[PDB]
Length: 12
Length: 172
Image (cartoon, rainbow over all chains, first blue to last red; front, side):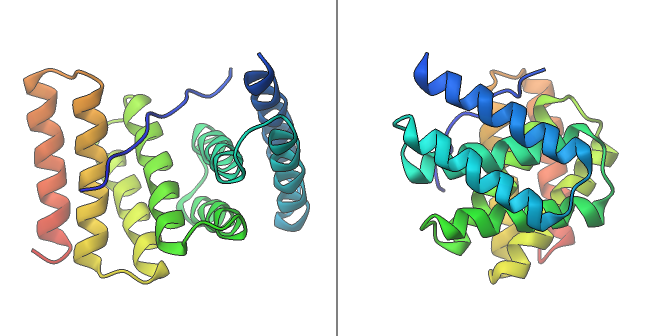
């Protein structure tokens, strides 16, 4: 189980 | 802010290049230049490559591209992550993670989410990991992201059932 960094939402 | 300013500039450039429909060579040159500007503004090299890849994959998913051109985009992202010192297995893992996290955040229905999962499994398998491990990685990414978004028990069961279908379709 590898921890995963939070996704960054894409600009409009 | 410096970091976010560079990120927005890179995003504009990558998305506009993709919208133009230019080939993968010109696209790779655009990604190189985006990573160079991110790196010039104090972002770690690996982190800059990661951000470029996420921008590319997220735009390509938003445009609703077919599975073949989408997996080509994924191969491009993996190649860039490789070129910036990321292990190929870790590179494919990151790209698949980007794709699947964006798909879950979009609220995409289950029939299409399973196709997205199968695509991530295809690229992980093509890199050189077993289908069982690749499906387990996909399921892991999906479950972790769903649990981190604070989803309710109902959506959690739906996610777990989707992941279990994936696993018993690809080696269990």
